[PDB]
Amino acid sequence: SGFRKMAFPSGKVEGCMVQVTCGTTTLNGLWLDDTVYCPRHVICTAEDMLNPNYEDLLIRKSNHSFLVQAGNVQLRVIGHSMQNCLLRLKVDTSNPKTPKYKFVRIQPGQTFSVLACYNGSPSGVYQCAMRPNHTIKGSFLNGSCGSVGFNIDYDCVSFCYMHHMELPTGVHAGTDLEGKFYGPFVDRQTAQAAGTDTTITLNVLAWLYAAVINGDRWFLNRFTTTLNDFNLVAMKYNYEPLTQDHVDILGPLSAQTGIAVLDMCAALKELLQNGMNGRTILGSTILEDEFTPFDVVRQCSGVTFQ
């Protein structure tokens, strides 16, 4: 029993974190095999960040312009190249702790674990959801750039996020491990701001299924709804439209609980229109949207508390 925002064990990632310094700028890097990946803005000073031309700034650097430190050991850079918004620093030693891994670009609404790091030293781990507006509500301080996001599938680490910037509202923006930003953001100091966000409908439904699996049905009702009628309510409450693909994804949870997807949608519609009347669901007083259908199946029992 219980239901918590649960991160994946971070050990496999901790062994890959290093520190990268260029000039007076230091941030984190990810060391896999003989390559260290880090934000390319490590080559920028606060002043360069106003209007950096990375091609021009990088051509002025040599391999020894970069200092890479793994724990107490200094790694020697023997090559460098830029890939989108990341730098790939080839070093003379292969990381003996490299786990089996993959680079994946996650989609909006999906979740991942973040290993917050400073000076190449892991400091904390927590779960984040990629918001529909392509930002994440992380917890980062100066020096956290290069910290990574990941999911673990068996013993394979699927890296999906590298941290690059904080936006005006305190939320965060970054790239996948190929250096492509999530969202319309860029790695330069501009007036860019997070666009309007929306609640992740599929995740809210998944979590309501989790509540039933864990033994709570107070919020269910005798009604059903069509996808279109549900979506009229979703637009009013700033929820993403429900799609048939979402309905299909919810099949396994619907099967485990015996509650048809559109019937759970009718329950959600009522919760949105009437509120929760002082009650809680899985300990929460609000509708949680940062657990995916996969997250629920991962954490909840496979047997419903009927």
Image: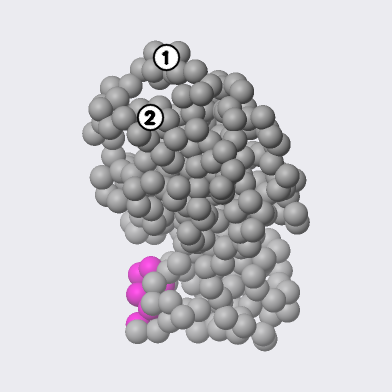
| Residue drawn at (75%, 54%) of the image | 155
Residue type at mark 2 is: Gly
Which residue is more in the foreground, 269 or 55?
55
Q: Is residue 159 visible?
A: yes
Mark nearer the N terminus (1 vs 2) = 2
Secondary structure state at the residue bearing disc 1: loop
Residue at 55%, 56% in the rendered image: 113
Front position in the image: 105 or 282:
105
Location of mark 2 (residue): 23
72 left or right of 53 in image: right
Q: Was residue 272 drawn as part of the magenta stretch in this picture?
A: yes
Give SS at disc 2: loop
Answer above or below: position of 274 versus 187. Answer: below
The magenta segment = 271-277
Other residues around mark 1 within 10 Å, as few (<14) / some (14–19) / many (≥20): few
Indicate left or right for 280 with 6 as reference. Answer: left
Q: Amino acid at mark 1?
A: Arg
**Disc 1 versus disc 2: distance between alpha carbons?**
12 Å
